[PDB]
Amino acid sequence: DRINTVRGPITISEVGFTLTHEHICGSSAGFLRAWPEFFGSREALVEKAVRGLRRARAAGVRTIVDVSTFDLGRDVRLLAEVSRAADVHIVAATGVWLDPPLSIRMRSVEELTQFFLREIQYGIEDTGIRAGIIKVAITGKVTPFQELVLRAAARASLATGVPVITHTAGSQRGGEQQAAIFESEGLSPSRVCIGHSDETDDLSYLTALAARGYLIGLDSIPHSAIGLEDNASATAFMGSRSWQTRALLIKALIDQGYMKQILVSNDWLFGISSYVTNFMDVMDSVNPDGMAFIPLRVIPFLREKGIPQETLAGITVTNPARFLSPTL
Amino acid sequence: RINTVRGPITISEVGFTLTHEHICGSSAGFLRAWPEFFGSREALVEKAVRGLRRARAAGVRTIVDVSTFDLGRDVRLLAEVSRAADVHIVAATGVWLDPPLSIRMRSVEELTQFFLREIQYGIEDTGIRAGIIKVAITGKVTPFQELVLRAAARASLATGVPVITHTAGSQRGGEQQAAIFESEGLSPSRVCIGHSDETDDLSYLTALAARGYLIGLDSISWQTRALLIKALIDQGYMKQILVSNDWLFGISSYVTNFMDVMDSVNPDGMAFIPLRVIPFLREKGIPQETLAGITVTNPARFLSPTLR
Ligand SMILES: C[As](C)(=O)[O-]
Ligand SMILES: [Zn+2]
Ligand SMILES: [Zn+2]
Ligand SMILES: [Zn+2]
Ligand SMILES: [Zn+2]
Image 1 (cartoon, rainbow over the protein chains, first blue to last red):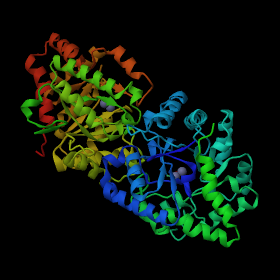
Image 2 (image 1 turned 120 degrees about the vertical axis):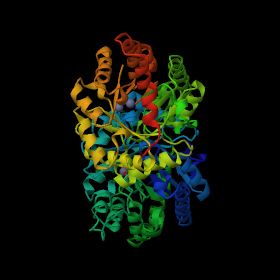
Image 3 (image 1 turned 180 degrees about the vertical axis):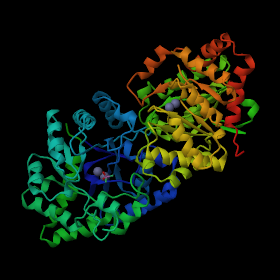
Image 4 (image 1 turned 90 degrees about the vertical axis):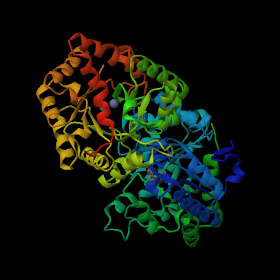
């Protein structure tokens, strides 16, 4: 139950302050290799990211989990290069996000399970870098293909002990659908983070999942298009709720007794091609702190509301370690 | 000169060409992320080299691999197979039916520059340059497909490389394609309107040929299909005909083991044209020089970069 990173296995003691939902680059499979000019250059992306991670390291971050799948253009060589140069642990992922190509979406639950296992048990591409988390996504009512992905994720998790992290669009309360399928496969809720759960203020929804032992991904705290009302693409991607509003859900879950079920992140990136052109600039305008936003802005905000330092250390260090540590 | 995955070649070196083929039909990054889907990369290479050597022994000298980025083109795979089989392979840019978000969110201007990158600079970090632009079409042409066609036209106008289309979603889609290409100022002689062998509407095909378009037939009943080649010859448009198999040696973009279905239907693979179609046409009285025009002269004129 050491944890696999892009630099190899590390012990739980070394994981430290973890951001469990981030991205070096949000893209599409092969796109970084075929069109680096889109990002200025690969070299520019590598530097921009390295600088960003280093600033997160200065603010106390020791590990990030890059939840980019194959179809979100995960380039594990970009992750390894940036991890080493920033000296920050990066856990990579398998799974399937919202843009599977035909070679993925035509696959069977059995085939998908085998693919996830390859990426966990053997390595990603020809690199030997093994995934440490499984990635899944739904929007709205689960599609037949998304249900296959969820079942394959559960089976791969049961075989390897690595956890599952989900994209929910909304809520839209997607966690209840996901949890039902995961449990039908015998997966323990303690192996699952229901992500983008900071999109909603439905505390009944959040607390009921937490009470079942799910981890709650309050993972996009700095995402907000307040002030950018004239930019429809910004509003659609980041929403109209303030970062403080998202952050207060952390306090709300603590106050209900569920501190141990909380995972906090920025869901930041250093490049993005999967959306509108130059969207990285729009996001950067909203959060110049990048991935340092959690430790620099959110932690002090929560301490200010009277949350004890020890509880914040538990959410940022202990919870991610328990989550990431492989457990059958 | 024409760019191949082994560098530039002269027109005289091109020889008998199959202008619409694939080594592998897949998705971007897939071959590398899950080569075991194909058994192994090594197995895919071995099969592709055997199949290309078979085609070469039946007279083929060049294939045009019209796999785009989104059809999982791997020019390193193409280079390896090309070298081992001693068959020239022309690589493609463009957009097929499965663009990921990073492609389908792009403007006409952005796509134009990406196609130009792949033609003028090279594919990925390989220095291998695309010698053709690829556009897949459905139905009457979707808005996004129209964007791709216009970018293809603009990249062609800047470089002289031709454009080949293929239609899956069937209508008289060639006329809509032609209208878009012509609105951009593209010469029809730079365009192969593909898989025209799907229909049996000779008047439609003849009218496109008379306008200067190349007519892309393919496919692997095949005899009825082959008789359209003769019909177009007899209309006076042998110069406008291109013939290919649209074959591949691996496929992951459809159902599992579809490659087995395909191989059971057409065990000749890419040799189907020279082993079956060419003798059939010779038997129906098409002369040698005409067959050589279709298989050698037409592809060379089509592929040789020109702005006219
Ligand atoms: C790349 As996302 C907006 O699903 O974290
Ligand atoms: Zn997401
Ligand atoms: Zn994300
Ligand atoms: Zn086609
Ligand atoms: Zn094809």
